Amino acid sequence: QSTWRDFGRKLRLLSGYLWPRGSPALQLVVLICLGLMGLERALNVLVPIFYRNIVNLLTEKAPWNSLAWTVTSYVFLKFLQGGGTGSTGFVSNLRTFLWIRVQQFTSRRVELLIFSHLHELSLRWHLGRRTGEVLRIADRGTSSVTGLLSYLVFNVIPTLADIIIGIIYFSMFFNAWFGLIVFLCMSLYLTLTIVVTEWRTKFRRAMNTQENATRARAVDSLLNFETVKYYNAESYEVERYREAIIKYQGLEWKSSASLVLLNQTQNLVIGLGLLAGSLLCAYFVTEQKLQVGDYVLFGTYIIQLYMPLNWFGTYYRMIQTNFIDMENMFDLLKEETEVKDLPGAGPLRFQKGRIEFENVHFSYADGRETLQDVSFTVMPGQTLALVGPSGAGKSTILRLLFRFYDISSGCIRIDGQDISQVTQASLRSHIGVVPQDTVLFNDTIADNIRYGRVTAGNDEVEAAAQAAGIHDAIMAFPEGYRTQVGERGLKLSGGEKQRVAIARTILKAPGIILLDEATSALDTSNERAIQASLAKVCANRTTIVVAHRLSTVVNADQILVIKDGCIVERGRHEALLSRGGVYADMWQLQQ
Amino acid sequence: QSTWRDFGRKLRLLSGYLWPRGSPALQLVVLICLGLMGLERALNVLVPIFYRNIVNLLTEKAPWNSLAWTVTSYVFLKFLQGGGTGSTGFVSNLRTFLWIRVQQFTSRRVELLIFSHLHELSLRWHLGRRTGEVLRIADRGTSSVTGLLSYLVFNVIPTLADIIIGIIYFSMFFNAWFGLIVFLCMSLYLTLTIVVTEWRTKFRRAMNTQENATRARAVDSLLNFETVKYYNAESYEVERYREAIIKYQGLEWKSSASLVLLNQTQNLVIGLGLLAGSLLCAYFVTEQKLQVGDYVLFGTYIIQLYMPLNWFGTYYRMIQTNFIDMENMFDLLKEETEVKDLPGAGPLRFQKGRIEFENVHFSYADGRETLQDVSFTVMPGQTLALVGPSGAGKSTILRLLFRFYDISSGCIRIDGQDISQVTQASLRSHIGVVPQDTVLFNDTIADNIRYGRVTAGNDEVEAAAQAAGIHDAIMAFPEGYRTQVGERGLKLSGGEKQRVAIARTILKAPGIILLDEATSALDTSNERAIQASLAKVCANRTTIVVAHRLSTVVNADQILVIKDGCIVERGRHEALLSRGGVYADMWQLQQ
Ligand code: HEM
Ligand SMILES: CC(C)CCC[C@@H](C)[C@H]1CC[C@H]2[C@@H]3CC=C4C[C@@H](OC(=O)CCC(=O)O)CC[C@]4(C)[C@H]3CC[C@]12C
Ligand SMILES: CC(C)CCC[C@@H](C)[C@H]1CC[C@H]2[C@@H]3CC=C4C[C@@H](OC(=O)CCC(=O)O)CC[C@]4(C)[C@H]3CC[C@]12C
Ligand SMILES: CC(C)CCC[C@@H](C)[C@H]1CC[C@H]2[C@@H]3CC=C4C[C@@H](OC(=O)CCC(=O)O)CC[C@]4(C)[C@H]3CC[C@]12C
Ligand SMILES: CC(C)CCC[C@@H](C)[C@H]1CC[C@H]2[C@@H]3CC=C4C[C@@H](OC(=O)CCC(=O)O)CC[C@]4(C)[C@H]3CC[C@]12C
Ligand SMILES: CC(C)CCC[C@@H](C)[C@H]1CC[C@H]2[C@@H]3CC=C4C[C@@H](OC(=O)CCC(=O)O)CC[C@]4(C)[C@H]3CC[C@]12C
Ligand SMILES: CC(C)CCC[C@@H](C)[C@H]1CC[C@H]2[C@@H]3CC=C4C[C@@H](OC(=O)CCC(=O)O)CC[C@]4(C)[C@H]3CC[C@]12C
Ligand SMILES: N[C@@H](CCC(=O)N[C@@H](CS)C(=O)NCC(=O)O)C(=O)O
Ligand SMILES: N[C@@H](CCC(=O)N[C@@H](CS)C(=O)NCC(=O)O)C(=O)O
Ligand SMILES: N[C@@H](CCC(=O)N[C@@H](CS)C(=O)NCC(=O)O)C(=O)O
Ligand SMILES: N[C@@H](CCC(=O)N[C@@H](CS)C(=O)NCC(=O)O)C(=O)O
């Protein structure tokens, strides 16, 4: 009693996992599946008993008909039970085929749960962890839980149960010494298998690691084809690749040899047990203590026990690795940040459109605070701009306005309504934003510009395309609206991406339009046509913008200049030139 | 005789493949391995004969000692042959362990051959094919050839051979009707397996394709986390993912059910054959025509035949897919471009350093020729520049100078030496070039700036680092020279990349230094320090450059302006301003 209470709640949670909590018929499928597994374990003893009975009736003179009937019964059981390999039988195969429905339900439920829980985390969690490996953890976790349940319920517990049935049949119906032989032989076999597998796993993991390094050495060398052509180094690249190959062979040989040693040890143990049992059984049956078929029964029973026990090592490794992998996935599932939550849940009301700041500090980086009590306010229809010395402070201002991160000390309200207790669905309904640079994922134009809401209609979406004028390029595409777009599809322009963005935010029709402008190269005339479209979508809508151009500065109804989280200049475009602060110096460098 | 002559030369080439053409002992290993395979096929008949002999001596009254000796011999053969037919016995396992050396030689040779042949192709071939899939073809080809040889030599030919031995043993030593039963049963079994597998492969491939699509729908949705957070579409993303899951289940169920049907058909056929054989054998042995152990012999022989024949379907699929995959790899191996080759092989001599052009046209794009008879010449030490209206013509001029592509009509010589018959090793020895933007692959600084030649020494490479002044940033790294660098390693600056480039070309010490400048953002003072380093490495060296800045234009000793492959302006910086062509207009827009 050392490792008992730790595994209990985890095994209880997995016990909750396999049983469908609400499904009507799936639980019946589970019960009938376990019933078939039990009946197959019955067949594993009831076949060779009939074999002994056949050879007993044959070895003495018997009538033809009764012997024929029992032979038919024997070959019938050799059909219902598997011919060999604990599979290939009308009972185990029907168990597998009838089992395949519940695995679908289990996999779908667990994997959709983990997918929703990845989309519920906050932004700050994702920027820390490498996104290229969380995916692997989740996928391997789902495959791990289905594999672990399948293996450890249907191919390890039945085998050990069959060992126990075996020791009992021999002890109760044969001499005790036969039970001693089978017991000692199978216990020794299991102990040798366990020890050698836990020794061999080191070579296994070292081989895998070196394999992933050698393959990478090559993909990169071919991809940098241009550089290796430059520097006249083909022979050097080939030689270094050969060295990586040689090291990989030097590990793989060790792994394969260890496998052979394990296999030969197992075979020797079963052969030794078979020799002892066959000799002793022969001695009794030639001393008239037993019957002729008992030797045949013992031979076929040892072979029948050995055939599924041969695959014990790989089950042991796979249960170990999926167990630790489920532990990692379960750890990630319990991990949770969700900074934006309040149980009061008072959704936002839109009545004016006033954006007011009140003395808020902020530190997404630890220690270095990037906000010193900035405070301003706007009226409905007001257009604000934010330009100053280079820094991510304005971008963080937008992101904290969007309830990505949290205020540190202070509060920001919209229309005098505190944003702390508002549901985020209500907030992201009221707000809308064209970003830095949009990313358009692999789909057609039609649904991707329908993406602004679920209920987007066809007439509405062609109406919005006419509103923001993509239709010329859309007809310039081969099939038009059904054009496949993305990394799989066609490459587009950054101006086209901003056109997509203004289309989908038109479809959203937000209260306040936020903008975040990039340094994408475009001619000024088309840039200002896009600016006119943004001006008309923000017409009678309050607007906060970051800008980099002179017109995009001078359009401001309330400019603001900040650096390192503090307000330094304010007013308008003409007033700050007459003031001649850093605005006047920056304006000459924008020429 | 329809598909005989087509397979002959391919099978002859694979016959050349397995046999090592020069190795002394590997051929001996191959012969001893085939000898062990033959002896194992002998054991597969010699075991159950002894089983029948044991039960025959047991069923009559026999002395203890002789029976004990033959029982020991039987269990001994059950050790040498697999306890369970398959790879579980000393005769076969030693074959696998002793075989593992020749597979290393085969895999290393074929995969290094294909790697060298990918590095021998020209540049124009790579820009056409997607590089993201040639890699898959090569890797799967090498794994295909080793798998195909292993499967089709060691687990299909032996099984069919064992079937033939079986029909003969029964026909020659038993009644002819037993041979008829085993023949008809195994022929029917093979035909059913073949037909059902070739029917099932459709569901297999459809399941794989839908699987790769569903997974991709998810990785992209998580990666665009920011956009899906913007547009308030978590529930929509989850729902669309659930639809993809449901379609995937709707295919996977069909595949699994087809597998179950195949397995049950196989088991039913073997069970039916076993029933017919056991009944008829029982009738003869109760009519005194045979001996008691003949029933036992037939039962164990049918089980021994069935146990390896159960795995026929997956061998059939895997031989089919690796066969077509080896065909693809072999097609790619025979594919070859190698535009730069002449058997005369007259290497370049460097005596002056004069670069002369003589009336050459060029068309890397078909039809649209991008070179109209450009011709000029330089003296040793001359510095040339190439700036004009935007176009890839200058870049192609450098690339054709480097013997990437070919001249179309005309010739270009260096120092009056024709570059057509020069060996490319001689050319790339004499020439050196700093490129557009270098790529530095995953290694340390030390060998990556040693990369300019194989014989790079430690004192030389620290000397070159002192020469080009990276040493301050190198000590600014954590451990200094052993810093791991790349995508795995640290990110660096573009100026640092150009420093690496000037270091490795210093180490090369070429005749003519070519440069190709990018639009990387850098301050002018450090840019001109880098320019001074390039000026001193090209000091007393002829130089051809593309430029974008005023100083990088006015340094030219012989300027040249081209557009769409034709020469339009020439002279120097001052002369073309006085001429006032497109040079004067472009110079005002460079301000
Ligand atoms: C889903 C679980 C399984 C996996 C992942 C698996 C994996 C593999 C793989 C990758 C091979 C190719 C040969 C190799 O890699 O050396 C293979 C072959 C084989 N598997 Fe499985 N297998 C599984 C289930 C089973 C079961 C249940 C059995 C029967 C007890 C079995 C018996 C075999 C046999 C006899 C071979 C051929 C060995 C040879 O040709 O040398 N496998 N398996
Ligand atoms: C979930 C798993 C662990 C269930 C395992 C079930 C076994 C522990 C038991 C339950 C029913 C038992 C069977 C019940 C009846 C029979 C028939 C019996 O055949 C006879 O000839 C007995 C009657 C007689 O004396 O005539 C031989 C044992 C056997 C197969 C028993 C073998 C052991 C079995 C399979
Ligand atoms: C459903 C498909 C797969 C066909 C399955 C057929 C079997 C169920 C048949 C075929 C051969 C039959 C056997 C053929 C001959 C005999 C001898 C026969 O002997 C007598 O009738 C004794 C003399 C008498 O009383 O007339 C008893 C039935 C038996 C064992 C038969 C039992 C039923 C068997 C196994
Ligand atoms: C390494 C693994 C395979 C275990 C091997 C153990 C055997 C070497 C041992 C354990 C059980 C022993 C047997 C247990 C009981 C008996 C019965 C015993 O019988 C009598 O004493 C009288 C018999 C009679 O009068 O008929 C003779 C020794 C013998 C065969 C023993 C011989 C040696 C055996 C087979
Ligand atoms: C697949 C390729 C490599 C061909 C493989 C051929 C073997 C499968 C054959 C060839 C010769 C055969 C043997 C020829 C003669 C005998 C003796 C035969 O009887 C005896 O052992 C003694 C008989 C007597 O007393 O005369 C048992 C089968 C055996 C070993 C045969 C087993 C199968 C063998 C090895
Ligand atoms: C190498 C390691 C794995 C040990 C292997 C041991 C076997 C080779 C031994 C152990 C038991 C032995 C058997 C034990 C008893 C007998 C009875 C013995 O009967 C006699 O006739 C002997 C006495 C006499 O001469 O009258 C003949 C040898 C035999 C079969 C022995 C043959 C050799 C065996 C199988
Ligand atoms: C579906 C697959 C598994 C094929 C099944 C074929 C059987 C239904 C056939 C083929 C071989 C036939 C046997 C071939 C030869 C004989 C011996 C023949 O013997 C005699 O004529 C006299 C025997 C004597 O006097 O001892 C009786 C019929 C029988 C058993 C035949 C019965 C029907 C068999 C088993
Ligand atoms: N949460 C996703 C994860 C999907 C996933 O991880 N897919 C694999 C390919 S089958 C992958 O891209 N692995 C990440 C890697 O190892 O690069 C899911 O389970 O659907
Ligand atoms: N009999 C051995 C091996 C049985 C076997 O055939 N397993 C195969 C897999 S199908 C194996 O070990 N291959 C290497 C691996 O799985 O890593 C054991 O005790 O596990
Ligand atoms: N020629 C290389 C090719 C290596 C290769 O193709 N590796 C695989 C991974 S095992 C890869 O790059 N896959 C790319 C992909 O799947 O897109 C070799 O055989 O060593
Ligand atoms: N008995 C079946 C299957 C035998 C078997 O165990 N094969 C496994 C692979 S280890 C299988 O079919 N798995 C599914 C697959 O390979 O697609 C046959 O006729 O091939």
Image (cartoon, coloured by chain):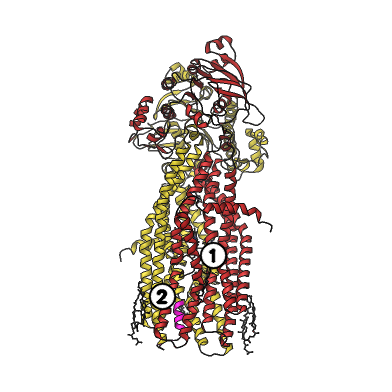
Chain colours: A yellow, B red
Residue position marked by numbered label 2 in the rendering: A274
Is residue B315 rendered to the left or right of residue A121?
right
Chain ID for label 2? Answer: A
Q: Secondary structure at mark 2?
A: helix
Q: Is residue B163 magenta?
A: no
Image quadrant assignment for residue A16: bottom left
Toward the viewer: B241 or B398?
B398
The reply to whether the C-beta atoms of the residues labelled 1 and 2 are less than 8 Å apart is no
Check the image and report above or below for B66 versus B209.
below
Toward the viewer: A174 or B502?
B502
Percent position of residue A540, x then y: 57, 31
Q: Which residues are magenta?
A: A287-299
Percent position of residue B110, x then y: 51, 48
The N terminus of chain B: image quadrant = bottom right
Percent position of residue A458, x then y: 66, 43
Tag shown at residue A311: none
Q: Residue furthest top?
A: B578
Residue position marked by numbered label 1 in the rendering: B158
Residue drawn at 66 percent across, 28 percent down: B368
Label 2 amino acid? Leu
Chain ID for label 1? Answer: B
